[PDB]
Image (cartoon, rainbow, N blue to C red; front, side, top):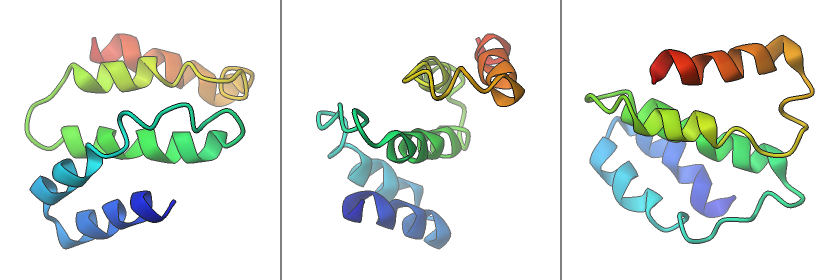
Length: 91
């Protein structure tokens, strides 16, 4: 949480390069979602904003495919519908 929090602060500063620099320290430290789903959701909801800046239209597809985590995501049709719609829209 500590190392993830300052990413939003850097976004507030509007310094994308530093955000992309600091984000690389969490890629290998996955499987933190075994008991903390909301932390994983918060993490994924930031690279979407980050990559939307310049032109990256395919990595965000990978993120939305990664929103296929614990059925605490897909058992909520009211938002699961658009969660699975946006991936096929962005492909």
